[PDB]
Length: 140
Length: 140
Ligand SMILES: CC(C)(COP(=O)(O)OP(=O)(O)OC[C@H]1O[C@@H](n2cnc3c(N)ncnc32)[C@H](O)[C@@H]1OP(=O)(O)O)[C@@H](O)C(=O)NCCC(=O)NCCS
Image (cartoon, rainbow over all chains, first blue to last red; front, side, top):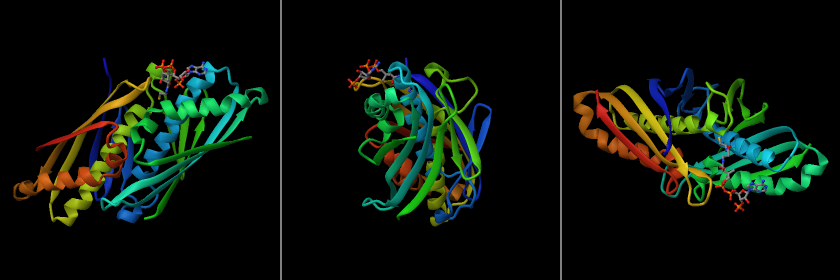
């Protein structure tokens, strides 16, 4: 009864990969700090961004469920990659700072909604205890 | 260590989000099972794909380190989402099957290169204990 999601990932050349998902094709490379090219998508930016997308889509469920009139949501993502005590690297922290536009009458529901969103977010769950995840917000 | 990676993610409408990294724009939405449109990227496909891209870029660092001559690399990724004992859902398993082309003389080095790639992959590290990760390969 699992829902199964499939994709393909190949080596182009050098430090360059191609992600294929349905009819979409994305170049995802090593970043400059590890010898890759400048100006491309990297796992280092794409993974935290997908985290922040999943957080937002989980929030949207709770937003509908709780009758919140959401006007806008913009989030800035800051991911820190650093040394692991197991050698090599790991994500130390991923910070997601959200600017939320809602009706004033809905503001009181937001702490709960945000906590729920992060709790039930599939990617948040995936990285629990291994990466510090700091989600905060301000009303605009 | 410490390197900072930044992105932005906004709500478009409905269950749709836009990822911005530099000048790159990517639509990432809930899947149809969770109220998103057909034919778009979803966190359920993108996140497993970025995991596989990270496995590959880590392997590429080790193959150069070890003098392995890599001819080709193709991988198929299957992600299975299901109910969580914590309520809601979680990724249960992500499988990555790699078809690797190498010089015959390099094949004896591949078990260790793959071990190292999986061990040091930072997205693999990020999901340790929370999602089952199954990586295997065949030569082509
Ligand atoms: C929403 C969802 C978590 C509900 O889970 P469930 O297994 O039915 O469990 P529950 O009904 O207990 O709800 C989970 C929590 O949400 C709370 N909740 C649900 N609806 C609520 C509402 N209308 N108002 C306030 N709280 C609500 C519950 O009280 C519960 O709280 P708790 O964690 O503190 O115990 C689940 O259906 C889901 O994950 N759906 C996918 C959401 C989605 O679209 N995500 C994006 C995918 S890309």
